[PDB]
Length: 443
DNA sequence: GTTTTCGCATTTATCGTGAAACGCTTTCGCGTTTTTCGTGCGCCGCTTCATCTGATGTGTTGTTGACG
DNA sequence: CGTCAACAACACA
DNA sequence: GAAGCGGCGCACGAAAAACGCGAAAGCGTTTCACGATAAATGCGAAAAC
Image (cartoon, rainbow, N blue to C red):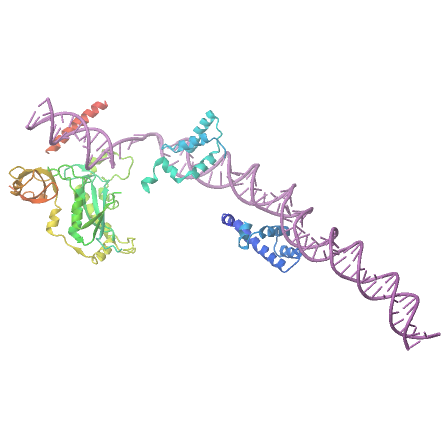
C-alpha cells in the first residue's frame, strides 16, 4: 500500500521534498550506467564526481528504493497521568464560570496535592484543551446554537423593525423612545414606507403596508417576508384596539406571506436626545433634552429620503454607481402592478374590540384619547333582525361620526351602522401610591 | 640386401565431470549521526478596574363576585 | 347556597 | 494609577530514522584437479621391392 507512503511524502516539509528532489536525478542517472553494464566503481565515482555526494550513501539508498516502484521513489526519499485530575480540570473549565486557565490549574494543583495526583505541564494541558473541540467551548456556553428565478421590483418586500435610542416627546406629552417599522424592496433596497409609534405593535406594520400599496400599488405576484426565525392592547381611541388576524388581510391583498441609525439616531439636531452607546450616562440631563415628535419625524423622513437617494451603493443593481432610487425607478417601470380600489383600502381601516349589541340593534363606542371625547352610539336594523350578541366594529377615525362597519366575531361582514385625562388620572395616582410606598419600604 | 608398410607401446592431451574457487553485487549489522518532536519556562502586550443588572406579549388558570 | 363568568395574576415563549 | 492572563518564541534532551563503514552471504560465473580415456605419436620388426 502506497497510501501511507504517499501521505508521508505529502506530510513532508518543503525542505524534505526539496531534499528528495535533489537526490532523485542522481539515483536515476546511476541506474542508467548500470544498465549499460558499467562497473559499479566507475559509475559511483562518476556520479560522486559530477554530483557532490557520498558514493556509499547513493549506493545504499539505491538498494533501499530498489524494492519500491519508480514513481514512488520520491515518497521513499522523503502522557500518562491521573485521569481523575484531567477529568477534574476539564470539568472545571466547562463550567459557565470559565475560570482563568492558570488559576483553575493552580486549584487543580491543590486538589492534586490532596489526592497525590501527578499532573502534566500547563502547556501540555492547554495544548490538549485546544485539541478537545470547537464544540466543547460552546458546550460550556451554548453559543454556536444561537448562531448556526427573476425578482421584479415590488415583487418581494421585507418588513423590519427598529428601536430608536433617541428620546422623543410624543404628542401626548410623554417622553419615550419610538419604534418604527419599515418595508423594503428586496431587489433595489429602496425603503417604500414607514410608520413610527410609542411601542411595537401590528398597527405600524399594517399602516406602513397601507402606505406602500397605496403609493406603489399591488403586484400580480406579491411576496412578503417577516423573519421570525400580535400587539393590540388598550385604547388610544378610548376604546380598545384590537385582537385580530392580520394574516388573513395580507393573504386577501394577494400577498404570499413568508416567515439609517446614522441618518436618524445620529443626526446633529437630536444630539441632546440620542445618548449613544454610552454605558455610563447621566439621567439628570435628559428630561430637558428630549426632542419634539415633529422634529424627530421630520429628521426621520429626511433620513429615509437621503438613504434612498444616496449614490455609490455597492450592489449588483447599482453597480457601484447608481442609488437605490435610480435602480428602483428603472426596475419598477418593468414590472406589472395594479392599483388598489377604495373598498380594499377601506377594509384595512382599524378594527375595534368586540362591542355588545342590544336587542334594538345598537351598540356603543366610547370615543376619547387623541380624538374629541364623545360617547358614540351606532345602529342598524340588520343587527336586531338576525342572530348577534357581540360585534367587531371597523372604522376610520375620521369617519367615526358617521359610518362604521359591523362584522361577526368570526369575520363575516354583516352591514354598516350609522351614528344616531380620564384613566390617566388613575394611572398617575397609582404611580404616586407606588413610589411613596416603595421608598418607605426601602427605608 | 635395401626400403616400405604394418603392428604394438608409451607418452601426452583433453574432456566430462564433480566439488571448489573467486568476484561481483546485495544486504544487514552495529556504532556513531542527524533531524524532529515535545515539554518547558519566561516575557510581553493588552485590557479592565479606581462602582455595576434584568424585561416583554399572550394565554391559561384560579379565585372571587354576581346572579339565579 | 351553588354555579358560572370575567378579571387579574403568574407562568411560559 | 496597576496587575494579571493569555499567547508565542527560544532551548534542551532524547528517541527514532540515518549515515558511513564494513563484511559476509547470496550467487553467478569461472576454477582447478584428478583422473581417466583416447589418440597421437614412437619404435621396431617383418614383409615387401
